[PDB]
Amino acid sequence: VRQTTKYWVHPDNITELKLIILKHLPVLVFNTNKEFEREDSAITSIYFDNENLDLYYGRLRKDEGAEAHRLRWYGGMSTDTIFVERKTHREDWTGEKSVKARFALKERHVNDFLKGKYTVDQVFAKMRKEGKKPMNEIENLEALASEIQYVMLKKKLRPVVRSFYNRTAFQLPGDARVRISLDTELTMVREDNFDGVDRTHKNWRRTDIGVDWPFKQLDDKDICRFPYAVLEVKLQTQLGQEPPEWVRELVGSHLVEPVPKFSKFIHGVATLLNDKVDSIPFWLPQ
């Protein structure tokens, strides 16, 4: 049985919270000398929606099958691999869950792919040629890309909001019993042109910022500097036991504030496009 929960963490409780976790879990690092630079922690996502904000409303109301679409990269602006990600909301008798699917695209192909000029076949030509991945897996990835490209064109999606944050990942590899992420410097930035400002100049992302938090060059109206860290806890508890006592103690402690449905996408839209949206998540006033 797997459970996911999200919490806010006041800046005054961040260090103390880290000390508790690191007592039990290692931090993942991605260089072999186990040294890391400032940009290594960065994760940036460009969320797409249309001018009616169809996707925002779908995710807000938690419609069955409501999709969120985002283009994500890890690290700094030299990063060339862009993840085209789709999150789907699911509900049934067993309860709730989030389903994520993604495929990878070189940066220089992104615009052209989104316009339907660069086809899915073209996208996966090198992958098929290589013969590394089994054919069925390739055909299923291509179906994913076709579905995403179709919605993008069909619903006229465009860049709307960017989330940026630094993520620390606490996890002992090959052990999913407990996985914890702490996101700091959380920021949302406008990427839309809804007020007539062509923020991306028809690129898939603005280029007047990189990962240079705190992004002092942005106009105040374009940015939301979130005050709290966001903590996410992914448990895979073996039926029919309970989650580790240190995990339970932690989540129930004064250190964290549970915000079950929290969503950086939804927070960004509601905060930055406040005069435009007609419904608001319940972690915000009304």
Image: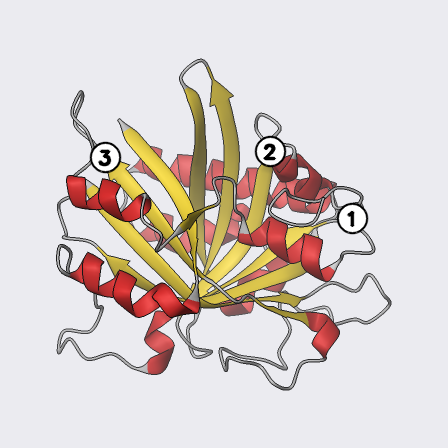
Along the viewing direction, whichever of 4 and 104 lies nearer the viewer:
4
Quadrant of the image for the C terminus? Answer: top right
Amino acid type indicated by mark 3: Gln
Quadrant assignment, res 148? top right
Quadrant assignment, res 11? bottom left
Closer to the chain start, of discs 1 and 2, is 2
Q: Residue furthest top?
A: 93
**Mark 3, secondary structure of its residue:** strand
Residue 266 appears in view: yes
Amino acid type indicated by mark 2: Ala
Residue 178: x and y in percent read 21, 44
Q: Which mark is residue 236?
A: 3
Mark 2 packing: few (<14 Cα in 10 Å), some, or many (20+)?
A: some
Q: Which mark is residue 277?
A: 1
Task: Name which residue lies at 34% across and 33% down.
Answer: 136
Task: Name which residue lies at 57% across and 28% down.
Answer: 65
Give the residue number, with chain letter if any, for mark 2. Answer: 66
What's the coloring here?
secondary structure
Task: Name which residue lies at 42% across and 46% down.
Answer: 6
Q: CA distance from mark 2 to mark 3?
A: 25 Å
